[PDB]
Image 1 (cartoon, chains in turn blue, green):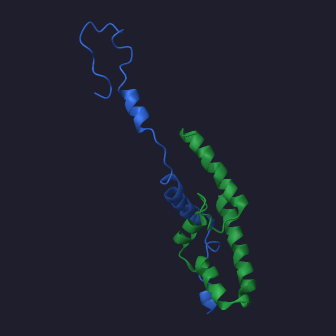
Image 2 (tube, helix red, strand yellow):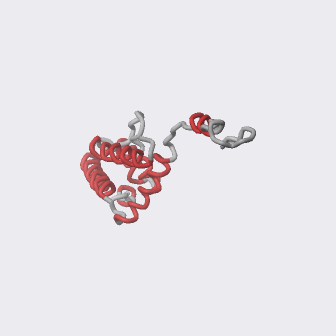
Length: 67
Length: 81
């Protein structure tokens, strides 16, 4: 039961090992779970013809970045 | 480096408190030593679960605020904020 109480804790590990474990855990728990929505804004920005008819193309409408 | 040093100091302190108060109840000791007997990876994962409002993580408010400052600084650097 002495070992059952004294199983390996995190503070027994060296600093660099625990830092690596923290990096992986922080990644998975925070960076992956972070969610921001930009798809509609990006698509509408890419679909905008930016001053193209004012621009001297001397031809039919040029394809916009989404096209 | 500093975040993990503070967290390790915290968990040594909490482990000392548990090893002082084990005589309260044997069944209490099992559910309080789940943390110390878990593998080191699950250990850091459940020490890093103070995001959102579930708040079952045993992390203190100060150590929580350190990461709830660094994470927003990093998001501002990344362009979200």
